[PDB]
Image 1 (tube, rainbow, N blue to C red):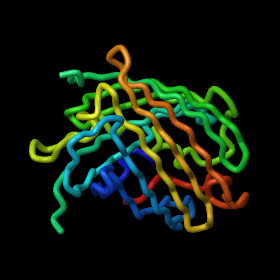
Image 2 (cartoon, one colour):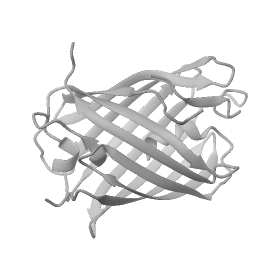
Image 3 (cartoon, one colour):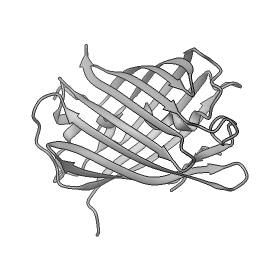
Image 4 (cartoon, rainbow, N blue to C red):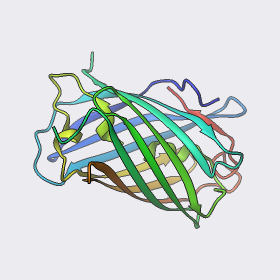
Length: 223
């Protein structure tokens, strides 16, 4: 299942005065098969901020609870930066997220509330499908779209995400699946009244109707 999910390594690199990332992995299928995905993200602070060198964010993301039709979902994430081997952010911080989405022309809206310890690599979120539920596609494609402020960075790696506040940062992501499925995500992260505000736009297209995403045959992300 989706408890105690394997570590996923997001490979961060400074480029063109932005922080970019690449992940080459996939979704485990219920029949033990493999569904390959490449994720490319650009993170850019709303103001000039000190960029780190290239480094790795190790991510453990779990679905820890859900109701019968995944219209209510609880996610847990533990993330910490590490080196490659070759005051306004408090110890406790809440977030709110609003996602407007379409996958293969199915429109949906998700509202969520999260909290965590941004220096101690821990966050949880409760997500509610407020429109277009239950979703006629795998939850797994949404899980990574719901929080870069909650990554524990070592002393010697500048924390690009925490340094960007209170103004915050934007990110743009493409997920390319091996079967022509593609997701484009635009996100705005801000800080208002001591709470992180996440606004997410998501467009997924070209998913095979009989594929693992539209048929909900996925069983979480692979290492």
